[PDB]
Image: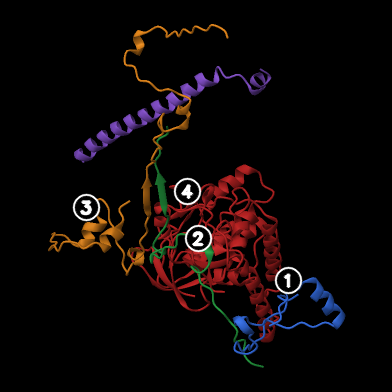
Chain colours: A blue, B purple, C red, D green, E orange
Amino acid sequence: LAEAATDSILDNPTTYTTSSGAKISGVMVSTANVMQIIMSLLSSHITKE
Amino acid sequence: LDKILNVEAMHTVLRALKNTADAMERGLIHSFLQTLLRKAPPYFVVQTL
Amino acid sequence: EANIFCTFDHKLSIADVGKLTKLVAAVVPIPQRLHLIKHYQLGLHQFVDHTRGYVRLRGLLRNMTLTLMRRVEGNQILLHVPTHGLLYTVLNTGPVTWEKGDALCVLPPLFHGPLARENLLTLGQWELVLPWIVPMPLALEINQRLLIMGLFSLDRSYEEVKAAVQQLQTITFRDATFTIPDPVIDQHLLIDMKTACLSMSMVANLASELTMTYVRKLALEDSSMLLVKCQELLMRLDRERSVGEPRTPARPQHVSPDDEIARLSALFVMLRQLDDLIREQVVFTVCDVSPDNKSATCIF
Amino acid sequence: GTFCNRLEWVYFLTSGLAAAAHAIKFHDLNKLTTGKMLFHVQVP
Amino acid sequence: MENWSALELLPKVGIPTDFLTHVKTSAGEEMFEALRIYYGDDPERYNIHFEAIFGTFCNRLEWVYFLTSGLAAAAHAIKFHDLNKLTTGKMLFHVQVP
């Protein structure tokens, strides 16, 4: 689902970078129920930063 | 060209001698393997014995 | 569009590219007028068929497209179609002399008589056969001669037409003798004979009554050498028509200038309709001829 | 809108496909007909 | 066939070529054995072809010997120069039983 979307034309690389130099490709959103299910499910690939 | 023919004669004699020695070595290995295999019983014979 | 790239499935050795590099500015036929073409349909080798009809090869060749051979470089050919109007150069191998002033046509090649059968390209079974480039009077001569061969030879046994065509197939044109290989009759040749008979029937019909008797008048007036031959021909045709004496002509009654204008204009229309069987349109108009008669510069 | 300015470039030797190749630049292929390598071998 | 490109391209030797008749008169009446005449500027000299013999490759055979192979581990390779003068080599063993 994530790599299916094409890129934007303009992308400021200074903006929306995290700590430790990691750069954001996109943002996804669900409701709280699906979010809690994913948080309990894929917690090894989740990081609060 | 006479020197070329002389060095070609020397090199075909040398190459034939080297190929003959290599064939002698391979034939010694082959004859030893034949004489080895002509007295080896199969596995089930010695495993039974 | 213009520059047409061809290829080869087989490799060329140094001999093959050597005999290809003397074929620059030679005209080759292409049936397709496409860009990425292949060498088996190049030339006439896919279309050549002995005992099939020379007139079939003639019609398909005059229907085929033409292009010029330039700049091989190894497994590439670079055919370039000549644009209409601009001066180009040509290089013919057909053993026929040329002229700085005449025009050209393109014909399927005949055997000259030495019978070389090597046009300096062969790939396995596949060979290259080049269409002969022929000056205009020889072109219309061979066209009219195959037309007489097709028109005469119907409903005749083999011996009389053989005695006709042993002297009819030979043409001596500017110290060069040519013979037609495959004169075999065609349904297309039958429709040429159909147009021929309808046109000569129409010029028989609407011709004036004075022109039907004009050569009798000039016979009674003047005696010239070509007139003597014409009187020989016409009186032999008359005695094959009628053993009676052909009467002298008197004052013609129906004299009318608009009548002659109308009937002779329709007559000229019908002679155009008959001549366009044999009169082929030109393909090359000579600007210059090389002194060894190998190459030329022609404006088309 | 704006132009399709996000174009990028690729090279041959940056690609690993050149590991299957032995790239050689030689300015006379148009004057070259064939390229042959002939091998001699005696058998043991 | 004589490649006239090799004549049109190689540097030649300057010679005051003097013969009594005209050039074309000697040419068309065939005093010589092979001619090559073009009346224009023939571009057939300009294109050159190769064959590109890149490399000739002999074989290097692997020089496998007896003692280089591990199969000689089961062998006890002795050299004995008078081998053709023997008939057979017998071996005797004497065992009394435990």
How far apart are labels 3 and 1 at the CA level? 98 Å
Which quadrant of the figure contains the N terminus of chain C? bottom right
x and y percentages locating residue A26 in the rendered image: 70, 82
Q: Residue at x 79, y 83 (%)?
A: A29
Q: Nearer the viewer, residue E98 or E32?
A: E98
Count neighbours of disc 1 (C-alpha within 10 A) and say few if under 14, some if 14 to 19, many if 20 or more.
few
Tell me the SS state at disc 1.
helix
Q: Label 1 is placed on what type of residue?
A: Ser
Please tell me the numbered disc located at residue A44. Answer: 1
Tell me the SS state at disc 4.
loop
Looking at the picture, does residue C163 appear above or below residue A8? above
How far apart are labels 4 and 3 at the CA level? 29 Å
- Read off the residue under disc 4: C117
Q: Label 3 is placed on what type of residue?
A: Met
Label 3 near label 4: C-beta < 8 Å?
A: no
Do the dots labelled 3 and 2 sit on one chain? no
Name which quarter of the figure residue C255 lies in.
bottom right
Name which quarter of the figure residue D2 lies in.
bottom right
Q: Nearer the viewer, residue B28 or D39?
A: B28
- Read off the residue under disc 3: E31
Relative horizontal placement of residue C121, taking residue D2 as reference (left or right): left
Please tell me the numbered disc located at residue E28. Answer: none
Count neighbours of disc 3 (C-alpha within 10 A) and say few if under 14, some if 14 to 19, many if 20 or more.
few
Label 1 near label 2: C-beta < 8 Å?
A: no
How far apart are labels 2 and 4 at the CA level? 50 Å
Q: Chain of mark 2?
A: D
Name which quarter of the figure residue E23 lies in.
bottom left
- Read off the residue under disc 2: D19
Label 2 near label 3: C-beta < 8 Å?
A: no
